[PDB]
Image: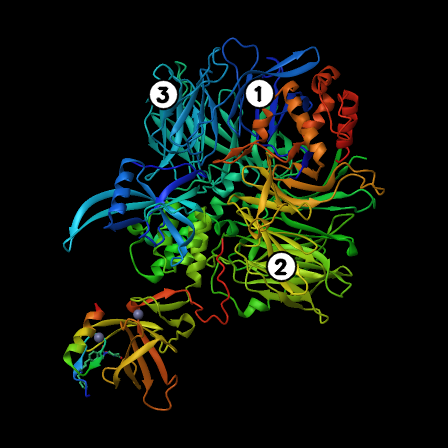
Amino acid sequence: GRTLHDDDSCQVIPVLPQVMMILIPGQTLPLQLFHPQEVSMVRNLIQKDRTFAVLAYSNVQEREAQFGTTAEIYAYREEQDFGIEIVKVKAIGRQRFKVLELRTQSDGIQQAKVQILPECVLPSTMSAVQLESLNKCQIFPSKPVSREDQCSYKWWQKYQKRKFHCANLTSWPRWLYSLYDAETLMDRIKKQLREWDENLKDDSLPSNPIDFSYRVAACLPIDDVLRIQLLKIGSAIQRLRCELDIMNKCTSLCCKQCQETEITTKNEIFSLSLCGPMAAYVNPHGYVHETLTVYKACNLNLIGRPSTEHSWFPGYAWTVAQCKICASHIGWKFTATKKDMSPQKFWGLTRSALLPTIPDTEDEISPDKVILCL
Amino acid sequence: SERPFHCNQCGASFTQKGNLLRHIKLHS
Amino acid sequence: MSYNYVVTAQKPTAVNGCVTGHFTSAEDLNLLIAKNTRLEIYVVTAEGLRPVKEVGMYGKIAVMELFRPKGESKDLLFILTAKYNACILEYKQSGESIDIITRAHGNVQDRIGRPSETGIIGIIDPECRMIGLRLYDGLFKVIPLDRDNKELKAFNIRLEELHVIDVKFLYGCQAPTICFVYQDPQGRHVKTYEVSLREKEFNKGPWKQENVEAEASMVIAVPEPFGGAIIIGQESITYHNGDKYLAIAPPIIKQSTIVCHNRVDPNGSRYLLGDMEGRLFMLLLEKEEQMDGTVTLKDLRVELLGETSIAECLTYLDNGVVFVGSRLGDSQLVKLNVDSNEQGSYVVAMETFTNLGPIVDMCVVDLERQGQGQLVTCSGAFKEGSLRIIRNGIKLHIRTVPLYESPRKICYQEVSQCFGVLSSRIEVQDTSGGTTALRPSASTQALSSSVSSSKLFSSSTAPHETSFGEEVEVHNLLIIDQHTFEVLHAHQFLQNEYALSLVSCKLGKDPNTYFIVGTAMVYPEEAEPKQGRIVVFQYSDGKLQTVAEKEVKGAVYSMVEFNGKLLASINSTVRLYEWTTEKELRTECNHYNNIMALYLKTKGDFILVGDLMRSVLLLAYKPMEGNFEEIARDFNPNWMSAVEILDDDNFLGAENAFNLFVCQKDSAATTDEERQHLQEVGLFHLGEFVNVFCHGSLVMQNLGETSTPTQGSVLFGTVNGMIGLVTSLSESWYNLLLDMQNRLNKVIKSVGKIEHSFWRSFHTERKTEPATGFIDGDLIESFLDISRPKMQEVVANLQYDDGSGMKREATADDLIKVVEELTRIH
Ligand SMILES: O=C1CC[C@H](N2Cc3cc(C4CCN(Cc5ccccc5)CC4)ccc3C2=O)C(=O)N1
Ligand SMILES: [Zn+2]
Ligand SMILES: [Zn+2]
């Protein structure tokens, strides 16, 4: 079934030592166990509550953690892979908690006294001024269930005026209440995720904002130390707000493959022709590339000599460019042939090889701390 | 050093065959 | 740790319910009005309304219905509070002693259950067989009406339809039948179920589901002759009774949305209808006796009667006299003339009952006495927009100044003997491209007028257009004389410019006093604001001049005077400006926060900051460093409505479910962890929604310090017009007055037998704890109204701590003089 503790209660539950990655509630965790004490300890959990702790480490090398997530096992199977006899276990994140004590046992397995942090659920912001006669005008005549009719901000505009009609009884306008409204915040995200990657919004994302906020915290392209901030937030509203602030702070692009190398920033983008900054170009072998033009990029190595052969930008010669770290292909460096060419050198990055990320300040000369918003 | 081993995907030139094979595998 | 005392200065004035019936005696006709926690009982005379009794409850009155079960002389009153307290009340008079007795009571709350989007709905079967409550989605609570059920034991019934919008009990049905409009994916529909008290279950109704209009918002049960029901929507009025389904959209109604109704003819032939804009209609149900005695509905006709105040509820009394219960403006009595007047209106106002409406801002001014302060508020909305001047009678004297447009902020500029007020009026898009006003209001009928020169965003303008008919609100800064209260000047802001904050102060070395407004360019596609101004105005010689125009990156939610500098909050930044000698604003400091700096109160070098989710944050200006440094915080998510600095260590805020809370700077703070965390030391369920906090007192401030028993004085205005005052106490008084509260609770007769401790218990949908750090001043001051025998019951075996040695039996006469000391704070 489902084993769940009460809010704000102290619980003492074991921590698996091999685990280190942050577990967001809702997302699934598969594990591979070889050690007998790990297996024996998991076997005992199947008899009892089936729940263990997955910490959110701030420094995994020192094993420093202030919060984490409980994990409920739901799948157990003693498999064999590569001539090794291993147990494969699947668990799911459930409750959040605040780390209190980290007593380590006689085994390598260590116990953890911890206090369950509750999921803070707030009623409608306008519910606070009593559900009176304008209440019957609060509910909507269904949704348009149309991708094109519900993108109509004409619908989202009628949504705001009607949901927050009572805004004039308070000291703040309707549009401020929209900035704290989950459905609005959710759709603000969806519109920006679809901007990053085209995909079906209906199937891929859950409709519940608590499920939505957590699901997005998992798939956001961010460091797990930054992800700890999202794990602390108890209100799906503040969580959705924070994720929007992050999304707006992801102004740079890194290697999609290694994700350790900041290539370029959005500032460096530019439209070479009226075609746009990004366009789809073809090579002489039938390969199609969505190419982004940027003035400056770094942490790249060049391959081969420049060639004008089948150049997408006449007057420029391309040189294949790849990531400094993993050598996956990132694009091309375009260099002008003549002196009267306007930028003289620029870069053509293929989109599928890039991934947006927050500009890191690995230069410790000016490391101003990133402040997330609620 | 005339690099007659070309990748049809990105265009990289290579000077021996087996080096290009290492390359086209990273594309996947 | 903090000992605070809270008392009502003005009871809630807004009306949120009203019914007629025979509650006092079977003969005379009663009118019962609900004003949040107050309940007023009248008798309908031919002259006007004769007040009879006025009682308060320990709860926000959510349901109020009269009914006469079989074998009763007069009607009984059923009330259901916001905390789900149920009760049946009887009017009892013994010569001239009037008392409301509790026939039955109980709490009907369910552990587990989602409070419906549509709120609490309470309906009583017309045969008084039962009471139905729709409290949670998917459930229907039924209280069977037996003489036995004095505890109101009830049962829920599985309700397959989740999103129910309204429900009523139908007349002339074999079994008690309910009719309701619900929503599911296919649109809205209307359905009926029979209620079986024997089976404790649902059965098939008289006439199955039928499809209704998209905006069906109201259900009216039509009395016995007709049967069936009328469903009112946004553009249609329909009648349904199985065989027949008639729906009309007469052109006279399409322009507005109907929000309330009341029955005129007792058989149901006529109904009164009021819309959101103050209009008043009459609905006619044409009959046909068809021999037998079977009256069948033939048609529906609607007539426009006139304009009233924006009606929350209506109730026809008799002889064409109608009570208009209003929430945004003054409630009224109106006469319905059969023959129109010269304006065309068949309605004429008889009486006007003052409603301090929604108080959205206020300030205290001494104005004339130079000793006794006066409170000027921003009350009401739309055409009900108004100012109010409250002062002590020298009881409360209130003078009204109508504006006919919504006032938003107010502040006082003594230097020019006038007030600065931010207001907004609605205009409609014109076919020409411009906009057309709806009526003349304060901003339109001003002596002098001006519009700010389109400069900053004249070049930086986004391309978008407004369709014809769209309502668009225009913002103004009003200058109002502090004596006559006429609009001396009205400055209109740029199009799409939204005025948020307003202050009046002196800056830097400049001796001129300015009106500073923080604005925000609000666009529809732009979700968070990216453009705004801080304008400095100067009012000199009857004319308003723009002094400086400082662009910012976002919305200026708040501003405060901060020791000669202008402290503004742009989104999450807390920016400090300086007034250069060249009369311009130069940034000195920034502090980038985790939260949007919406609420801002300041005391010296402390700054209290808050966002909409009860995130409290305490900053401090470091003079040597020349920038801001954070002191402490307490982020517990919950809706927050306003906030105020009590003293250097206490902080007062108002949060969700009509609660009050006090956060305190942790004494015995040794770690930087606990130094930087504020402890919640006071929690209190006020019952009102606080919009604004204000330092000041409506009493003679008292020059010579006459050992004031309380320290501090904070006023606050609420949504229901209630004005309250909060003041701090000493440890011995709090401990004493607290024991006073618990003794009074034993001798005091509660209306509906609601436990006081339960009423004030801190409550939200998830968490419910008892109140701490707060004294119910209204309970203490009620000690003076009981009898001396009840006082001797209260004081019996009660000690103080005066000297920690002279604790003695408090006499009722010692104690009486003590409460009198507390009545003098308001
Ligand atoms: O601007 C851009 C970016 C580069 C991109 N290219 C170019 C490209 C050419 C080839 C083949 C073409 C045929 N030669 C034969 C040859 C040998 C010696 C000298 C000249 C010719 C081998 C490479 C393979 C892949 C790519 C590729 O991805 C593109 O099309 N346009
Ligand atoms: Zn890489
Ligand atoms: Zn390649």
Marked residue chain, label 1: C
Which three-letter amino acid code belongs to the residue tagged 2? Answer: Ala
Residue C404 seen in the current view: no
Q: Nearer the viewer, residue C147 or A96?
A: A96
Which three-letter amino acid code belongs to the residue tagged 3? Answer: Glu
Residue A115: x %, y % from top left: 44, 42
Work out whether disc 3 and disc 2 sit on a shared chain: yes
- Tell me which label, 1 or 2, sits earlier in the chain: 2
Which label is found at residue C194? Answer: 3
Residue A243 seen in the current view: yes
List the residue tagged with mark 2.
C568
Marked residue chain, label 3: C
Q: Nearer the viewer, residue C792 or C528?
A: C792
The residue sitting at 48% across, 50% down in the picture is: A178
Residue most extreme to the bottom: A339
**Measured Cα–Cα span from mark 3 to mark 2:** 61 Å
- Tell me which label, 3 or 1, sits earlier in the chain: 3
The image quadrant in which ligand 1 is located: bottom left
Q: Nearer the viewer, residue C798 or C200?
A: C798
Q: Nearer the viewer, mark 3 or mark 2?
A: 2
Residue C501: x %, y % from top left: 63, 55
Which label is found at residue C752? Answer: 1
- Tell me which label, 3 or 2, sits earlier in the chain: 3
